[PDB]
Figure 1 (cartoon, rainbow, N blue to C red):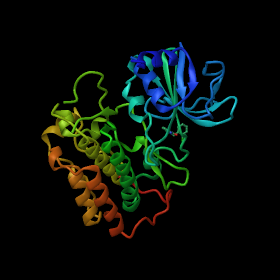
Figure 2: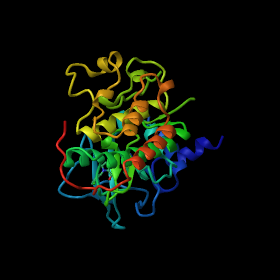
Figure 3: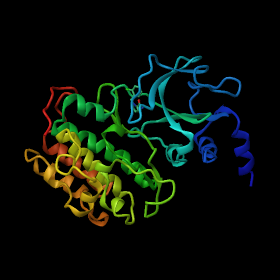
Figure 4: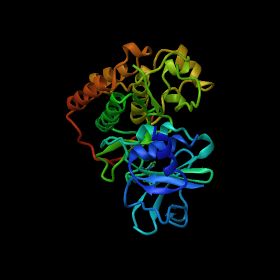
Length: 323
Ligand SMILES: NC(=O)c1cccn1Cc1ccccc1Cl
């Protein structure tokens, strides 16, 4: 009843505020307005404008698949964080409604969001270790113990999202980000995220990474929290091998082979310990009913880590040649 008025008070300004107000406002995003959740990112006379109140680090350098993520600084407070640019015309409301209010050390904190013209500018904590994706390229591929350690932390973030009926939608090394010493990993990018029930190919849908798609996505069957778990194990194989599943063996339209072919358990390295191999296999079952949940696999993975003597390799050790 007052809902309508609260939304209007938020439009046309940028304000210091809370996550519930950011979400409210973001629902209207299908000139300069938004909500900032930390006093470190501070508006100035109802505004927060790129190149006036905040400055991207120079020269411009772009991380992410679309080069859409930048280091920035609030001109008044000196606070540094990261900004992800999303184009307004393709903005998915779930990207801010999902993460808004979330609080978990396995999920990268959201610091605010400001619309300015054809951009939505999403702010978040800046994690200097970079993406797991860029660790893989830099190191070639990762030791079994480190890969387990990171899969498990991804899976912990997923327990937290899945418990609250949120699907991440594009779990992969590029969307896990690492603290500066490498010991903490955290899920980033709610651009493909989704609010769940206990179909998928309809509406505002942006599909995830093809190589990490589960079969129920691909064949258009009913989908659920289990689709993240498949992805997480494709990511595992990527950490271990230095390449995504499927890319080595099939060349044409990949999504056809994910449907018809057996799951890609042949890509498990043979020098992997028994329980590592088995954990990955249960996360890669083709029917969601037989696939492990986040909680089941996280548990399995944590004992898999224990079974190889725990985490012992240095974070940026020596280069392992890929497959
Ligand atoms: N939340 C982040 O920090 C983030 C999200 C996607 C990539 N990153 C890392 C990153 C982004 C911009 C500038 C420097 C770095 Cl190390």
